[PDB]
Amino acid sequence: DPVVLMETAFRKAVESSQIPGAVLMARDASGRLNYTRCFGARTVRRDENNQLPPLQVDTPCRLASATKLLTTIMALQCMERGLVRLDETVDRLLPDLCAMPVLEGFDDAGNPRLRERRGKITLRHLLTHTSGLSYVFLHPLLREYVAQGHLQGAEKFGIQNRFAPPLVNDPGAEWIYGAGIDWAGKLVERATGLDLEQYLQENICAPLGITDMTFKLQQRPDMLARRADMTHRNSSDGKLRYDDTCFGGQGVFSSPGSYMKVLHSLLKRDGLLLQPGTVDLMFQPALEPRLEEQMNQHMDASPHINYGGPMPMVMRRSFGLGGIIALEDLDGENWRRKGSMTFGGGPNIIWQIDPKAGLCTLVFFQLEPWSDPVCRDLTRTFEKAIYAQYQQG
Image 1: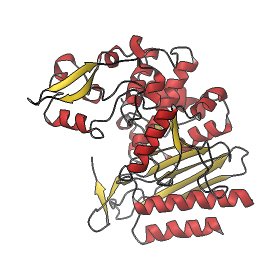
Image 2 (image 1 turned 30 degrees about the vertical axis):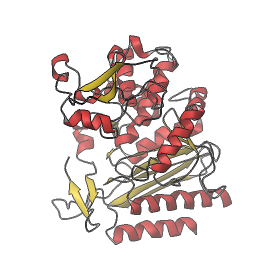
Image 3 (image 1 turned 90 degrees about the vertical axis):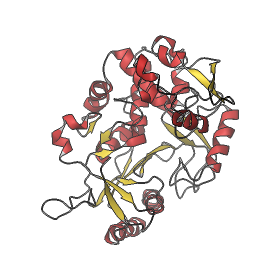
Image 4 (image 1 turned 135 degrees about the vertical axis):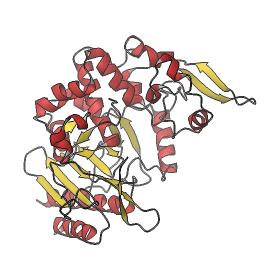
């Protein structure tokens, strides 16, 4: 009954040309629950035979911000192998990040005001967004810094634009969604002497038996020919449109199923990717009370951003290594529980791991912009329907 009505919903969301397609996956520890449903086409662009290729479980998707879980997993594997201490200064491996000044602001003459950072950066600061780094667009000062063209000097030191911006605050001063994970990816490459693509294969893909996961998609024509195209929703008519647009924070292309294999491993506590104890640490609310409050105050005040997605707009959350932790049950028993870690991806990608309930789910969409009402409501419905079936069943 709940699941059927939930599938009824998707079938009619694709029928109505509201969503290009969606991949719904749900797995539990025990093996009882293995839900996998494939709706619609992968692209809104009609093919050469005037058909619409379906969105299948084997379909390579642009993960975007969903890649940060995979990088976190890589960074923790290095830590697990004694290549890094979680609360050790990045100084040795990331001397570049450690050289970085902090943007105070600008003077009357428009010139930037910089300062030496106070306090050290650890992989934890990085993994928990407390590093002091932002994303250029997310920060007012950084946005101002970028338009007045201050990253013009980068060229002469070979500094990569991605890692060229300064710090906005001191480490552990506040929760800022930033380039912390892309920098952690750098550390992994620098600790192992392996590029993220090679490392991801060896350490993430190979142990779970994964093919449909890569950073360098172009080098896999096998996977390229089978990939989903990005769909955008007209801010104007709400119609769908075709859109043709080695960093740890975003670069990954993965099929829905291949991503699930990762999560399932994490849920099961199989020890395949990370030591179960190391996984338990990921789900720990990493934030200091001051920062736990600051984060929620900002998140409640930022519905335009909405880091939660399907999640209630106003709620008690903290952050751990790899995602946002529910510090309260979302709808008591009926849905997601306390200690549920989750994160998203730009094209309406949303994953979660509910250890308390013993469930993990993913909704794969290849549809921009983020937090799309249709997608959000559909996701809310899928999880809720699943939790309903699992509980009575």
